[PDB]
Image (cartoon, coloured by chain):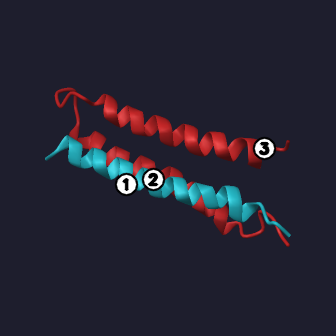
Amino acid sequence: CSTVSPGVLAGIVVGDLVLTVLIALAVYFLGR
Amino acid sequence: CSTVSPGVLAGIVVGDLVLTVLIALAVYFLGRLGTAEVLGIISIVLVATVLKTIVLIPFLEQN
């Protein structure tokens, strides 16, 4: 079938990646 | 032809939540009223919570 699971859930992994780069950038922004 | 069968995918959802919390907590640890611009941490935590929550609920929700 079209299988929705590999769609929305797939989107969650994508969201995690976005937060990974965004947050990381925030880490650099803070600076040690 | 299947749906929400993987389950592991669900594990991906949980993994994402703890991901934001772990890194966010890492930076928050150092921050302690003084670094200013702390609002940034709140911003990222906001888009994360609403992103998973908004895309995941309407779907995982029973209609």
Mark count? 3
Q: Do the residues at pointers 1 and 3 share their chain? A: no
Q: Tell me the CA gap for discs 2 and 3.
A: 24 Å
What tint does the image give chain B? red
- Residue B39 vertical placement versus B48 (above, below): above
Indicate the amino acid at tag 2. Answer: Val
Q: Residue at x 22, y 48 (%)?
A: A28
Indicate the amino acid at tag 3. Answer: Glu
Q: Do the residues at pointers 2 and 3 share their chain? A: no
What chain does badge 3 belong to?
B
Reading the image, the residue beneath label 1 is A21
Q: Do the residues at pointers 1 and 2 share their chain? A: yes
- Per the image, label 2 sits on a secondary structure element best described as helix
What chain does badge 1 belong to?
A
What chain does badge 2 belong to?
A
Q: Nearer the viewer, mark 2 or mark 3?
A: 2
Q: Quadrant of the C terminus of chain B?
A: top right
Reading the image, the residue beneath label 2 is A18
The crowd level at tag 3 (other Cα within 10 Å; few <14, some 14-19, many 20+) is few
Percent of width and height locating residue A1: 86, 70
Q: Residue at x 43, y 50 (%)?
A: A19
What tint does the image give chain A? cyan
Reading the image, the residue beneath label 3 is B61
Decide which of A19, A2 is in the foreground and name it.
A2
Indicate the amino acid at tag 1. Answer: Val
Percent of width and height locating residue B36: 21, 27
Q: Tell me the CA gap for discs 1 and 2.
A: 5 Å
Q: Are dots 1 and 2 in contact, CB under 8 Å?
A: yes
Residue B23 visible to the viewer: no
Residue B22 visible to the viewer: yes
